[PDB]
Length: 122
Ligand SMILES: CC(=O)NC1=C[C@H](O[C@@H]2O[C@H](CO)[C@@H](O[C@@H]3O[C@H](CO)[C@@H](O[C@@H]4O[C@H](CO)[C@@H](O)[C@H](O)[C@H]4NC(C)=O)[C@H](O)[C@H]3NC(C)=O)[C@H](O)[C@H]2NC(C)=O)[C@@H](CO)OC1=O
Image 1 (tube, rainbow, N blue to C red):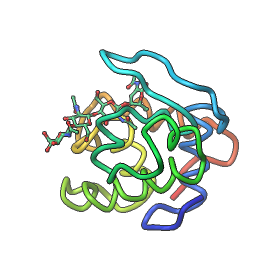
Image 2: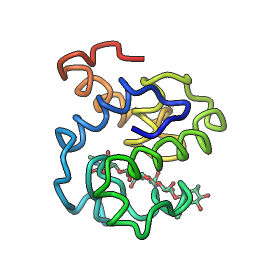
Image 3: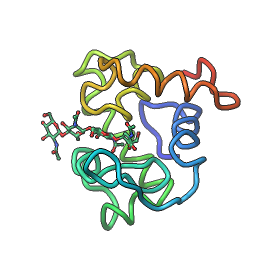
């Protein structure tokens, strides 16, 4: 995946959690479509710098999608006071700018750790 502050093992775990790390297309989630490898919504894609040729094109690319995650965490993680490890990055990915502080994402982190080789992933 793209390089950055998020580890490759963490990105792999998130990728597997969202789509079994496959280009699965989109689905509706609480008002907006989440797409591709990392199930990224348009707003997230905008916030990570509009990488790729378009939102859905980027989402369908493991590299572009992972770069978007890298940029999103560089933008919000430290700002929101998240631990700079997968626990914080995963929750930010699932809950937004301050996702690592939302109780809603506690379940996402716990479910993600159930994936082979993802328990306590950093
Ligand atoms: C069950 C489940 O959770 N499913 C999925 C969750 C997840 O999608 C994530 O969904 C959340 C909430 O809808 C997204 O959070 C929003 O993120 C926005 C983008 O950063 C953010 O909007 C920004 O907000 C800041 C602060 O106000 C502003 O300064 C920015 O200008 C603004 N940007 C824009 C372009 O509007 C917004 O406030 C968040 N909303 C809330 C309620 O927090 C989050 O981004 C989603 N994550 C992704 C990767 O898309 C995914 C994968 O887990 O899809 C799910 O199915």
